[PDB]
Length: 301
Ligand SMILES: O=C(O)c1ccc2c(c1)nnn2C1CCCCC1
Image (cartoon, rainbow, N blue to C red):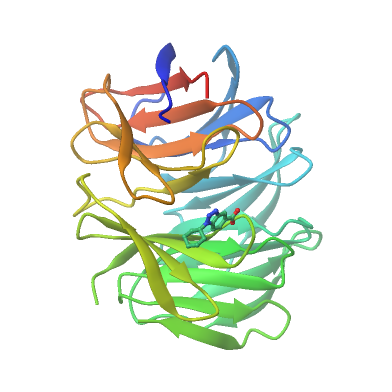
């Protein structure tokens, strides 16, 4: 059982490296962020360019959607996050408090909170409605590379170049577990909240059992020794792990067997980010400056 992702559209418009692509929860849009200081919105199905959202003073590392698909949050080298109304393109709030680049961001499922991680080694939890910081967690001893809420919002997982992943109780800010030293470049909870997928800068993805603090699966064969490359759980068809790679390919693994099931050829630079559509077997991928495009791919399974 293998997927058959094939290229459907190639999207161009950003003028510097893309950093992150994300499909809206309602499936209608793809958002992209870039070192060019811009967010772009594209039709998720035909790639049609929709709008540019602008206001950050420096490049953007990440963007994330609210559960109702109406809001975006972005994390910027200007040391702020911004909350955006997607329909109007307007900045609703600027979240100030980090003392260096903000690298990662996510809403909780309820979408009343945002979590951020920064070069400043902290994780912050913000109130969406007021735009004020509720908690600053002294989370890591090196830049924070990823932050993600679990399925009900009760926990946050963070990762850092310090080699650690940490699980935090959202309401209290207490660290409930540290997974233990290669730099960790990405982390997220599995859909059921019981596992955690982590990328490290030694060409390795790992699936950890949260309750046991133990690694259950590793996924290798790709190249990842430099860039923050996200990894995804693909769940609409076959159960895969999806990731970009520094050899210009999208890698897709069987989650259970760890075997590579497809390598998507087409980009001409590092595939820095990938995202999986919430209902269709559709992948978005973005590549670095020799390539300059976002590609949309479709599989029958
Ligand atoms: O939906 C999810 O979050 C999810 C999480 C882990 C899953 C899964 C679905 N299907 N199989 N596995 C195994 C991974 C390897 C260890 C035993 C479980």
